[PDB]
Image (cartoon, coloured by chain):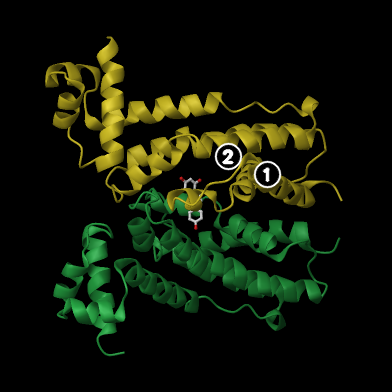
Chain colours: A yellow, B green
Amino acid sequence: AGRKMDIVIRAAWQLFLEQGFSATSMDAIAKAAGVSKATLYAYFPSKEALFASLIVAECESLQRDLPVPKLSAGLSEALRDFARQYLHTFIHRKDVAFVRIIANESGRFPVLARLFYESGPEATIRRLAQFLEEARAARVLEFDDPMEAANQFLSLVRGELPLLIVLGLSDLTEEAIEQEIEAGLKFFLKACQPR
Amino acid sequence: GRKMDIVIRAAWQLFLEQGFSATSMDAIAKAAGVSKATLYAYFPSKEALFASLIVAECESLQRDLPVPKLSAGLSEALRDFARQYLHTFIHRKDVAFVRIIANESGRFPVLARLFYESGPEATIRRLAQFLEEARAARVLEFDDPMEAANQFLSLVRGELPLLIVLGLSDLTEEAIEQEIEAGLKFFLKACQPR
Ligand SMILES: O=C1C[C@H](c2ccc(O)cc2)Oc2cc(O)cc(O)c21
């Protein structure tokens, strides 16, 4: 239906962040959003389905803010743009929050854990890997597996940032981001360019 | 010495149960059976107590990590270090500590950075010393040792910490050697003389 749905999502996100997923009840969500349990369960048949809707919405959205790298832009420039958008999504979006909420469930909801992984981090690997296939086909990178190589690129460029963010110590200027990206990219190319 | 270690353990218990902010020096003194006089004589503040806990726990986690010896062979040294490094992630040895700090939501930055510098950055510095020996022996090339140590650890760690924290990792010994070999292969393609 209508406007109470998006009020329900926002009310639920707030409670999941402050209290965790299992600690938040559909009862509390209904109260916070000012709907009957009838209206709430008509939109989302369970708490699990609600969190699933939230994961898929945020991950589909983060995926749209990511360029599709074109080799016509230059190899270095393509990878530098992708890296830059990838780190911006980390800093300015809910990935770390999602992981904190699921990690706090101590393995109770594996189906939600996998849904987040496959909609987000694995989706980002697959998008980069498609582009790394194009670049290997153009004989300008060499590697055995594109998914393996996409994971390596993202690991290099990401470094320890997710831990710094979770500890409240990531406070890195745009200039500091370009340095992280340049170092990861330099190293990826040292390993994958024909030599 | 005498009292201190009972106070440390009593405080660790309360920090885990209740969190750092929620725990009072009053409760720590009660739990350890000392006067507030005795407690404040050993420790200036709650912040100082947590600091002693971080330094002790990080020095201890650091002792479960080899010192890589170049005399053992480059690949073998790195493979042993990588293996012991990933064992820390798999047995969730940092997890409780990090949950306590992360739950303070950036209210205690000096404690957060002391944990970072005493633990994860300490691991980078140990590896960087070893990569300097290897560069001096002309069997790796790279511009900055700490940059290179961070890259090695990033490659070998990959996605594993995320899979573990989400409860989607259960790794056989054979799967760990494959993670290490892939990271090591890549690191050497980039740093070996060509
Ligand atoms: O793959 C990683 C690495 C990171 C991490 C890095 C260093 C460390 O010491 C602990 C954790 O944890 C994560 C947390 C995330 O939200 C997303 C991620 O992709 C990761």
Q: Is mark 2 within 8 Å of ligand 1?
A: no
From the image, tell me which residue sits under label 1: A181
Q: Earlier in the sequence, mark 1 or mark 2?
A: 2
Name the mark on residue A87. Answer: 2
Name the mark on residue B4. Answer: none
Residue B167 image position (x, y, % from top left): 37, 50
Relative to B126, residue A15 above or below: above
Q: Is residue B58 left or right of residue B30?
A: right
Among all residues in the image, which is located at the extreme top?
A1
Q: Residue at x 40, y 76 (%)?
A: B56
Relative to A168, residue A125 above or below: above
Q: Is residue A64 left or right of residue B143?
A: left
Residue B43 appears in the figure: yes
Residue B37 image position (x, y, % from top left): 20, 79
Q: Amino acid at mark 1?
A: Ile
B36, B173: nearer the viewer: B36
Viewport quadrant of the C terminus of chain B: bottom right
Residue A20 appears in the figure: no
